[PDB]
Image 1 (spheres, protein in one colour):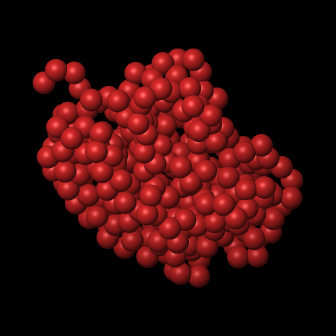
Image 2 (tube, protein in one colour; image 1 turned 135 degrees about the horizontal axis):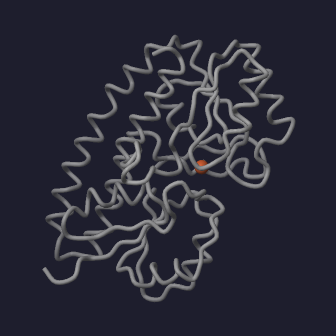
Length: 274
Ligand SMILES: [Fe+3]
């Protein structure tokens, strides 16, 4: 066992999933730090250094990292793989990014199985000497992810179907909302420039009042202020922060992809009184 195979990922969700597949035979690191906004992140010379010293670079694609393709052109002789191949996308419904794929495919545990398979295939292709470890680790991790779905689905099924409105800040939850039968309301369709402008807040306030939706949420890499303004002006309580674009730090409450899915579903369910 000389040097560990080095994988660099764009952001922390892919880092944790890939590290579960790498296990003992590769080290995986994320370019963005926990809590950093990932869509419009601005890479630094230090990020170039980290990617250039990797053996493999993984990214989401589906229009998540607006920075990645320009950044990767600086990187020489380091293979990359997009980890969302074979996932059917949901289009963004409104705004200047209307009609392109919603990048947040990982919030569906069924989709996470495809992420696992795509990351396995890339490690097996570019570090073939450890293919058996990658294959074993991916099989074990896919088992955990697969088993993850049933308790989540049952938990959220307790909410009456006609009351299943998921009101958030970024429209980051489209894939989870589809899986578990939630209607989707958000203050902005995808992180970009306009985030909490009028018209956006007003439309959400109208849908809240018309349907008497009981809770609204923010997310861990963006500002909670638009969501708290919406709850102050309506009957809805502020449900707290969901995790979608970043894990927490390793010593925080959301250190892993599994903990992120569980925490986000629990926080939603609590916002509806379980
Ligand atoms: Fe996002």
